[PDB]
Length: 31
Image (tube, rainbow, N blue to C red; front, side, top):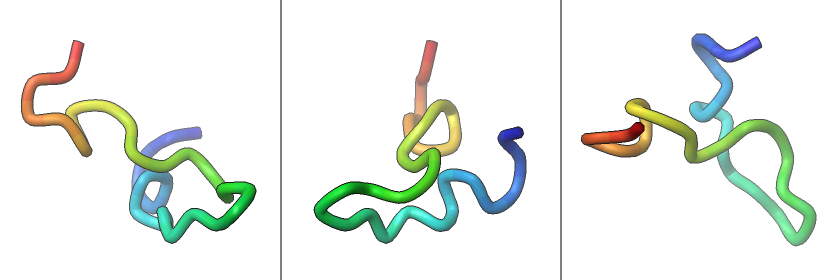
């Protein structure tokens, strides 16, 4: 769980898919 293709395979739908949009990966200054 969580390195690689996690937030990389976003392409969410009407019911989302996997762990998108997280963390320093998506945010420049996460917390």
